[PDB]
Image: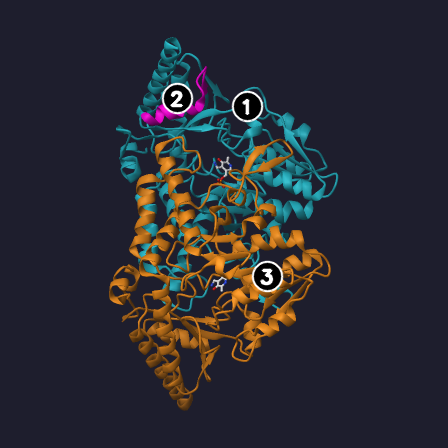
Chain colours: A orange, B cyan
Amino acid sequence: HMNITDIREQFPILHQQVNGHDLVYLDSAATSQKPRAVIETLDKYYNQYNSNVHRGVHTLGTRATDGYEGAREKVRKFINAKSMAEIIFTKGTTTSLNMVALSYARANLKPGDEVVITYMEHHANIIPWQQAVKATGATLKYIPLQEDGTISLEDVRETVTSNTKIVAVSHVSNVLGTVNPIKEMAKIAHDNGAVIVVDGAQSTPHMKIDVQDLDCDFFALSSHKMCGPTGVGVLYGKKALLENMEPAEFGGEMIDFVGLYESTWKELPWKFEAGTPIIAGAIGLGAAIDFLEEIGLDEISRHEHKLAAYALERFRQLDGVTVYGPEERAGLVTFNLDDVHPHDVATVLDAEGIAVRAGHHAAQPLMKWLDVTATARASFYLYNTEEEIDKLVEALQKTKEYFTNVFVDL
Amino acid sequence: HMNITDIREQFPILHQQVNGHDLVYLDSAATSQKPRAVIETLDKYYNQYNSNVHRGVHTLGTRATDGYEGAREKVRKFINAKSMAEIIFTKGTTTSLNMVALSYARANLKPGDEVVITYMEHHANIIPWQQAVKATGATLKYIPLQEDGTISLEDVRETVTSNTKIVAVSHVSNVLGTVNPIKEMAKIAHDNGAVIVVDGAQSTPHMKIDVQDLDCDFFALSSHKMCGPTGVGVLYGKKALLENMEPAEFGGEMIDFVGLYESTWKELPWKFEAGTPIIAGAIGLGAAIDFLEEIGLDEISRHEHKLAAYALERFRQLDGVTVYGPEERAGLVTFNLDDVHPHDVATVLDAEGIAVRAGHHAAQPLMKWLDVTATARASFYLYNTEEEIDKLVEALQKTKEYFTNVFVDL
Ligand SMILES: Cc1ncc(COP(=O)(O)O)c(CN)c1O
Ligand SMILES: Cc1ncc(COP(=O)(O)O)c(CN)c1O
């Protein structure tokens, strides 16, 4: 069982004050904090074995190469891919989904073809598809949501047709906390002749991923959300689909032969990795995976289930607070106070040391569906505790009273 | 005047042995090493103020944002751009040139249009243009080289015509060491109605860049070659051209309004930065710039001029060694030993602690022009010394004798 004191002692950034109060960081769905094992991995790389990779002519070059391809294997095992050929390092989930939209969608869509998404998607899993359908004359459709912000498989079956070529959907929503029924959606897509593209940015850090159980055709994730460095992500795709897609970017490292006018590509996965790679970041993301595997993804999901059930109960104790989304959920709560703008809520909470986010959370169509212009969101990870949730609910109570008193005075 | 002892004391990786001999790192044209100021900048970011950027709702978020946009200003000043709107953070020179090829070239080329490159280009400044001309039915042309591997402006004037829309050329070649006459080539391109795209990956680390003196329309560079983190680069473009180009990637952060089917973009530079950015890396590249500015780019270029004139003299002392390229050059020497394969040269030198590279150096058309299948390359930076060049030339002498003796025995 995970001990939260020992886990928090590994994260130097948690041990500081903001505005004279201990920091209470509740914004890991925007980005997560890093343990010493990850930061010291980057230090050891730049202090001891930095060099360019995939020459293997000299000793430090060999070490850097082994570190970078070593991390590719750690990612393969971490999401249970069959092969390192299916693991592409990218700059982040957004670039991974764009590569699918450019190299897969723009090459396989025709007038009459549909791409199906959902109203709860993050912009990273919306805009690339808007652009690919515009480029190809294909059509974009939205699976509707149920009233608690879940998706019914009957709506999926209704929306997806035999003209659908791509269904793209979030594993977990970073606003509603909904965990979507990806494995059954993948069956529905494949029954209709479509591939499924899964936006895993908010699932991967928080629960075990098995791409062979999900049967997703593509899956995208970001290191910065899962205790790893910024600037790095992964695109997984089934090897038979990657083999037939052309590269999204062109350059050194992803070529085999270059003539004056024509070139041939390397095999996977290097066909999709043009230029000097994100060497230190990918090695640090391998360290993040080792760190999270040592704790156990199931343990971290059990902890977050506890925190989310505690938070939802304690929010129901507050009068005049609306929480969006379903009762069964990932480790976050997006909410509004009646009559206080969420930006003011986040400002007041930061004065008490508490970091949360306010805004649209890069889900404008979802805010429109929720009929609000903005919300506040507290999000949790393996270093948070029930005490910090008490601080949050106590501060929202004081926020409520403070604005009430301001109103009364005015 | 720069003191090399004090500079080398700042780079922890130099102080180690390989194969029982002090390391002699002569492969900075593949990637450079980092000073403590840069590594400690990344540590301080992840230890103290990591958070997502461009919310400014909570205190650490504000600090991370200020750090990231602060580094954008350091880059603007470092290359003398007029505006931060012209400074886009990317993953590296290769991605920066691809963005030009996708968003500029593919949008502005028609049958009959030409893109002009040179035989000495790196693949990053070849393959994207091969693909953009293929996509548009335009034509690719090559400026020829003079016999010493320089470019004559008369050949430029011959090759560039009023059908040319893009001239793309390296500032400095990572194989020949040639510094190309970019400012005069930009005049020739603009006289013909073309833009010029400059591959600055090998110039920026080593000499001062002034984009307003060069008058280049686009300029690309990589952090990992200039003492900064891996995984980050810059695309500079003249603001009036960026304003008319569409984004190359789509997602959160680069939008203003998102509807179900249509979206509008943010202003520059954020229009070109989709998804959570490379926050720590860009802050570390700002630290690299501060480090190099404190030493002085002109001082670092004077040091490398010394090292290159010393190396070329000492290589001319070796019998049976061919050096490629011109006498006036950047800080590198690419060479072959007669009758020893360059891979064997690099292997033997690594056994004496000396790191150099062998291969095509991502310039296959140039190797074909040189009539060789591969070369060896020693490349220098602000932490190298004449003593290390003596070690290199002494080891190449011993390599020569060793293979001679092997031949004799056989
Ligand atoms: C002249 C030149 N151009 C382009 C590149 C590609 O830069 P990156 O690998 O950082 O994308 C390099 C890297 N060696 C280079 O030296
Ligand atoms: C569900 C979801 N999808 C996609 C993204 C985009 O990931 P990145 O900003 O790392 O590219 C995020 C980031 N918050 C997300 O939470």
**Labels 1 and 2: the sequence-earlier one:** 1
Q: Residue at x 39, y 65 (%)?
A: A28
Q: Dot 3, how many residues are within 10 Å of its Cα: few (below 14), some (14-19), or many (20+)? A: many
Give above or below for B194 relative to A191.
above
Q: Mark 3 points at which residue?
A: A127
Q: Mark 1 points at which residue?
A: B149
x, y percent for residue A302: 36, 69
What chain does badge 1 belong to? B
Q: Is residue B33 visible?
A: yes
Circles 1 and 2: CB atoms closer than 8 Å: no
**SS at circle 2:** helix
In the image, B138 versus B76, the foreground residue is B138
Give the farthest residue toward the bottom. A408
Amino acid on which the number 3 mark rests in the picture: Ile
Question: Is B340 in the magenta?
Answer: yes
Instruction: Tell me which segment is drawn in magenta.
Output: B336-351
Image quadrant occupied by the N terminus of chain B:
top left
x, y percent for residue B125: 57, 37
Give above or below for B97 relative to B371.
below
Q: Mark 2 points at which residue?
A: B311
